[PDB]
Image 1 (cartoon, helix red, strand yellow):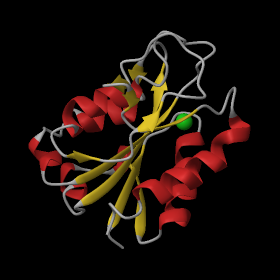
Image 2 (cartoon, helix red, strand yellow):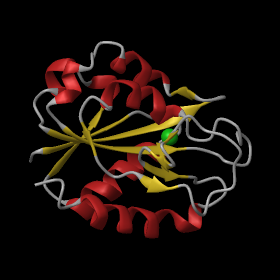
Image 3 (cartoon, protein in one colour):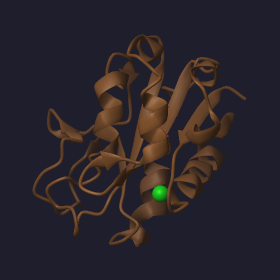
Image 4 (cartoon, helix red, strand yellow):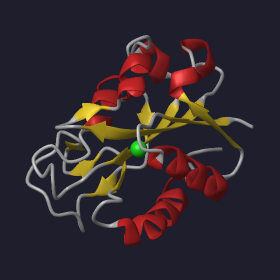
Length: 163
Ligand SMILES: [Cl-]
Protein backbone atom coordinates (compact mmCIF):
# COMPACT_ATOMS: atom_id res chain seq x y z
CA UNK A 1 0.00 0.00 0.00
CA UNK A 2 2.08 2.85 1.38
CA UNK A 3 5.56 1.73 2.57
CA UNK A 4 7.84 1.74 -0.48
CA UNK A 5 10.63 -0.85 -0.32
CA UNK A 6 13.22 -0.05 -3.00
CA UNK A 7 15.84 -2.63 -3.85
CA UNK A 8 18.72 -2.92 -6.28
CA UNK A 9 20.58 -6.18 -6.81
CA UNK A 10 23.15 -8.01 -8.96
CA UNK A 11 22.74 -11.45 -7.23
CA UNK A 12 19.06 -11.37 -6.30
CA UNK A 13 19.66 -11.50 -2.53
CA UNK A 14 18.59 -7.87 -2.00
CA UNK A 15 15.19 -8.54 -3.68
CA UNK A 16 14.62 -11.62 -1.54
CA UNK A 17 15.54 -9.53 1.53
CA UNK A 18 13.11 -6.78 0.46
CA UNK A 19 10.28 -9.31 0.17
CA UNK A 20 11.01 -10.85 3.58
CA UNK A 21 10.86 -7.35 5.09
CA UNK A 22 7.69 -6.58 3.17
CA UNK A 23 5.95 -9.74 4.56
CA UNK A 24 7.13 -8.92 8.06
CA UNK A 25 6.07 -5.20 8.25
CA UNK A 26 2.98 -5.25 5.99
CA UNK A 27 1.41 -2.45 3.87
CA UNK A 28 4.42 -2.20 1.58
CA UNK A 29 5.24 -2.25 -2.09
CA UNK A 30 8.51 -3.74 -3.36
CA UNK A 31 10.09 -1.87 -6.26
CA UNK A 32 13.27 -2.46 -8.32
CA UNK A 33 15.22 0.81 -8.50
CA UNK A 34 16.26 -0.27 -12.04
CA UNK A 35 12.62 0.26 -13.09
CA UNK A 36 11.79 3.20 -10.82
CA UNK A 37 11.96 6.99 -11.04
CA UNK A 38 12.14 10.10 -8.84
CA UNK A 39 8.38 10.16 -9.47
CA UNK A 40 7.95 6.68 -7.98
CA UNK A 41 10.16 7.51 -4.95
CA UNK A 42 7.99 10.52 -4.16
CA UNK A 43 4.76 8.44 -4.30
CA UNK A 44 5.67 7.19 -0.81
CA UNK A 45 6.20 9.15 2.43
CA UNK A 46 7.92 6.23 4.24
CA UNK A 47 10.60 4.03 2.70
CA UNK A 48 12.98 1.15 3.33
CA UNK A 49 16.08 1.23 1.10
CA UNK A 50 17.75 -2.12 0.45
CA UNK A 51 21.09 -1.85 -1.29
CA UNK A 52 23.96 -4.30 -1.52
CA UNK A 53 27.58 -3.15 -1.60
CA UNK A 54 29.49 -3.75 -4.77
CA UNK A 55 33.28 -4.36 -4.66
CA UNK A 56 35.18 -2.32 -2.09
CA UNK A 57 32.40 -0.15 -0.70
CA UNK A 58 30.59 0.98 -3.88
CA UNK A 59 26.83 0.94 -4.17
CA UNK A 60 25.22 -1.63 -6.51
CA UNK A 61 25.06 -0.06 -9.99
CA UNK A 62 21.25 0.27 -10.39
CA UNK A 63 21.13 1.93 -6.95
CA UNK A 64 23.98 4.27 -7.96
CA UNK A 65 22.13 5.29 -11.14
CA UNK A 66 18.84 5.79 -9.31
CA UNK A 67 20.35 7.71 -6.40
CA UNK A 68 21.99 9.97 -8.93
CA UNK A 69 18.64 11.37 -10.07
CA UNK A 70 17.51 12.02 -6.51
CA UNK A 71 18.61 14.97 -4.36
CA UNK A 72 18.47 15.43 -0.56
CA UNK A 73 15.09 17.26 -0.65
CA UNK A 74 13.65 13.98 -1.96
CA UNK A 75 14.40 12.45 1.45
CA UNK A 76 13.94 15.30 4.01
CA UNK A 77 10.13 14.87 4.38
CA UNK A 78 10.25 11.06 4.66
CA UNK A 79 10.80 8.30 7.18
CA UNK A 80 13.67 6.15 5.93
CA UNK A 81 15.01 2.77 6.96
CA UNK A 82 18.23 1.53 5.37
CA UNK A 83 19.18 -2.13 4.88
CA UNK A 84 22.70 -2.95 3.78
CA UNK A 85 24.15 -6.18 2.51
CA UNK A 86 27.83 -6.85 2.88
CA UNK A 87 30.62 -9.29 3.40
CA UNK A 88 32.61 -8.57 6.55
CA UNK A 89 35.21 -11.31 5.87
CA UNK A 90 36.30 -10.14 2.31
CA UNK A 91 35.74 -6.41 2.85
CA UNK A 92 36.58 -5.91 6.51
CA UNK A 93 37.60 -2.27 5.94
CA UNK A 94 34.63 -1.28 3.78
CA UNK A 95 31.88 -3.60 5.22
CA UNK A 96 28.36 -2.86 3.90
CA UNK A 97 29.50 0.66 3.05
CA UNK A 98 27.02 0.66 0.13
CA UNK A 99 24.31 2.14 2.33
CA UNK A 100 26.54 5.02 3.32
CA UNK A 101 26.25 6.49 -0.21
CA UNK A 102 22.46 6.39 0.22
CA UNK A 103 22.84 7.86 3.74
CA UNK A 104 24.77 10.84 2.40
CA UNK A 105 21.41 11.97 0.94
CA UNK A 106 18.86 10.13 3.12
CA UNK A 107 20.25 11.60 6.44
CA UNK A 108 18.41 14.81 5.61
CA UNK A 109 15.27 12.82 6.53
CA UNK A 110 14.08 10.95 9.57
CA UNK A 111 16.41 7.97 9.35
CA UNK A 112 15.17 5.27 11.75
CA UNK A 113 16.43 1.68 12.27
CA UNK A 114 20.09 2.18 13.22
CA UNK A 115 21.65 -0.99 14.60
CA UNK A 116 24.41 -2.12 16.86
CA UNK A 117 27.72 -2.84 15.29
CA UNK A 118 27.74 -5.75 17.85
CA UNK A 119 27.93 -9.28 16.44
CA UNK A 120 29.85 -8.27 13.26
CA UNK A 121 33.64 -8.77 12.86
CA UNK A 122 35.26 -5.98 10.85
CA UNK A 123 37.74 -3.11 11.09
CA UNK A 124 36.05 -0.21 9.29
CA UNK A 125 32.91 0.92 7.50
CA UNK A 126 31.61 4.36 6.64
CA UNK A 127 28.20 2.65 7.19
CA UNK A 128 28.94 3.47 10.84
CA UNK A 129 27.95 7.00 12.03
CA UNK A 130 28.09 7.96 15.71
CA UNK A 131 28.70 4.43 16.95
CA UNK A 132 25.91 2.62 15.14
CA UNK A 133 25.30 1.24 11.64
CA UNK A 134 23.02 3.65 9.86
CA UNK A 135 20.69 0.77 9.10
CA UNK A 136 20.07 -2.94 9.24
CA UNK A 137 23.14 -4.93 8.05
CA UNK A 138 22.84 -8.41 6.52
CA UNK A 139 25.79 -10.66 5.61
CA UNK A 140 24.58 -13.67 3.70
CA UNK A 141 28.11 -14.92 2.87
CA UNK A 142 29.19 -15.44 6.46
CA UNK A 143 26.09 -15.00 8.71
CA UNK A 144 23.28 -16.23 6.43
CA UNK A 145 22.11 -18.15 9.48
CA UNK A 146 21.38 -14.90 11.38
CA UNK A 147 19.49 -13.07 8.57
CA UNK A 148 15.89 -13.98 9.62
CA UNK A 149 16.36 -13.18 13.34
CA UNK A 150 17.95 -9.90 12.27
CA UNK A 151 15.05 -8.94 9.98
CA UNK A 152 12.46 -9.94 12.58
CA UNK A 153 14.01 -7.85 15.40
CA UNK A 154 14.60 -4.92 13.03
CA UNK A 155 10.98 -4.84 11.89
CA UNK A 156 9.80 -4.85 15.55
CA UNK A 157 12.31 -2.01 16.16
CA UNK A 158 11.03 0.26 13.34
CA UNK A 159 7.43 -0.87 12.79
CA UNK A 160 6.03 1.89 15.04
CA UNK A 161 8.03 4.50 13.12
CA UNK A 162 6.31 3.26 9.98
CA UNK A 163 2.60 4.15 10.41
CL1 LIG B 1 22.16 -8.53 -3.81
